[PDB]
Amino acid sequence: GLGTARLQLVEFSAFVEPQRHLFVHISQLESVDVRQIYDKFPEKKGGLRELYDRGPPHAFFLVKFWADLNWGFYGVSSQYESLEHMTLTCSSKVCSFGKQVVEKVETERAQLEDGRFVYRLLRSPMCEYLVNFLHKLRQLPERYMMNSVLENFTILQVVTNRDTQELLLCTAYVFEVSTSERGAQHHIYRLVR
Ligand SMILES: CCCCCCCCCCCCCCCC(=O)O
Image (cartoon, rainbow, N blue to C red; front, side, top):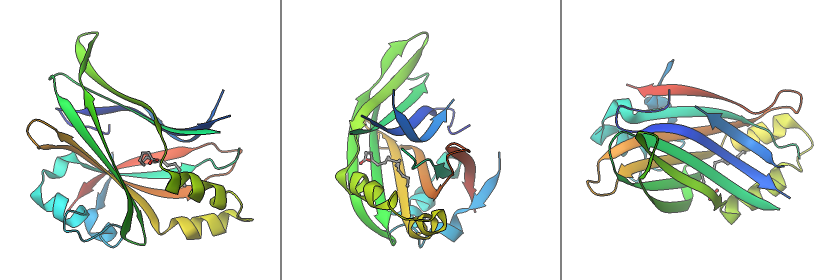
């Protein structure tokens, strides 16, 4: 799924606890042309266009999320695994109208477990930008209006081998809102060119 030979995403979620509520969730394949989502991130040029150019291309993914905004502590939990012992640097950049408004950098050392290495980045506090954005968003009286606002909101996650600075995974995230009857959903795509 979302991964390479060196590093795979095992689980991703963002949630609020007052039993808890997942806005989005991935627990653990088509293609999309990165071309069409440059405007959605900064031309840093450390932004998407620049990163996809250094490579490698098989490390790049796009995820479309249909978030459940129908519901505290706001948290993000991430888990990766690999067969090699590594220390990871995880960069998350929140962008609004192609401009970066948050960058969060975290480090996680491998933990030996059941014949492989796991990397657990759990219950990291969600940035306040997002908490405040979510409280506004859930106020909109129509889902079509939430989707219009979310057209301009994206996240770019870059996971690097800290000791070698090699890119392991780069994931672009885009968002719409789901209904309550249908839960959160996602679709994972390969980014190509
Ligand atoms: C409109 C739905 C979005 C709400 C859920 C956001 C899920 C992605 C959050 C992870 C990237 C941000 C960096 C980690 C902590 C943070 O939130 O600052």
